[PDB]
Length: 107
Image 1 (tube, rainbow, N blue to C red):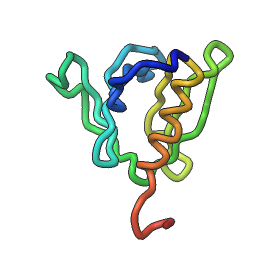
Image 2: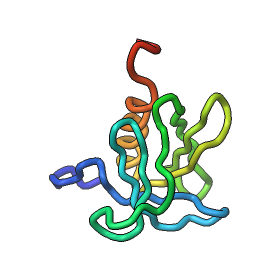
Image 3: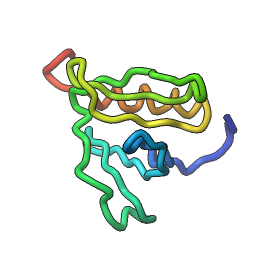
């Protein structure tokens, strides 16, 4: 949306679907893995990280927000995140995809 703000560090706030409920969660991707946090400054880890490496990020929007995506592992479900704006989801889609699949496999 707002094109003119530096200081993202691919560490923006995303909506991590939980028990059929969109709850605010801090998503941090690093080393081809999506870690989950709660407090600020990656104080504590919300739960086991994600092994994006291999997964598949597909744009699965909703009738209430066309800015939501989900990951899949060979057709299965791994997680589901939701951005705030279309431009935001567009940065995550490719961001994750790149991580999910790199090396001597498919390259």
